[PDB]
Image (cartoon, grey):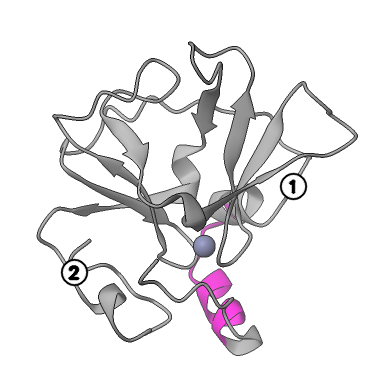
Amino acid sequence: SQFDLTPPSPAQRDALIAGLSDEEQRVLLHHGTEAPFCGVFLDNKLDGVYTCRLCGLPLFRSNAKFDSGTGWPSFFAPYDPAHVREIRDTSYGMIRTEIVCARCDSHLGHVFPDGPPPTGERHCLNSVSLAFTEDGQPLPNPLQRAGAETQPA
Ligand SMILES: [Zn+2]
């Protein structure tokens, strides 16, 4: 990855959190308390990139030509596998795993084992956790990181 996955500094984290709505804070900053959501993402242009609502990291690409299968919302694919972390917890075991932002550790969703082959995985993403950048538009880059993050995704 050309992105710097170093977490936000404490000051940066405070600033970004200060910009979140109550609903956004409920979703992004908590783990294991809220009901899962499997967003369908019907409200944006097909061609762009979903970013972590907290830290701006590009997470999921959508494109009219993508065909990742029925375990993902229509037209979705991972932006970079390094950008999300899957978490297994003995509280759930094989029932579900949590998906978090690899940079800021904010809650993104869950993976359930009831998806299509070959992975058998269903990616259940909370739309509140994600912002959208249309193709051609520079990434939000709230951390003001140099390099790829200064460009369109
Ligand atoms: Zn993040």
Picture quadrant where residue 2 is located? bottom left
Task: Confirm whether the magenta stretch covers residue 110.
Answer: no
Image spot of residue 127 (x, y percent): 44, 39
- Of the numbered discs in the image, which one, if any, rests on residue 31? 1
Q: CA distance from mark 2 to mark 1?
A: 30 Å
Residue plotted at (38% across, 24% down): 40
Image spot of residue 50 (x, y percent): 34, 49
Relative to 12, is 36 above or below? above
Q: Residues within 10 Å of mark 2 (few under 14, many from 20)?
A: some
- Of the numbered discs in the image, which one, if any, rests on residue 58? none
State which region is magenta: 12-22
Residue position marked by numbered label 2 in the rendering: 138
Picture quadrant where residue 147 is located? bottom left
Dominant SS of magenta comes to: helix
Relative to 131, is 40 above or below? above
The amino acid on which the numbered mark 1 sits, given as a three-letter code, is His
Image spot of residue 73 (x, y percent): 37, 25
Q: Residues within 10 Å of mark 1 (few under 14, many from 20)?
A: some
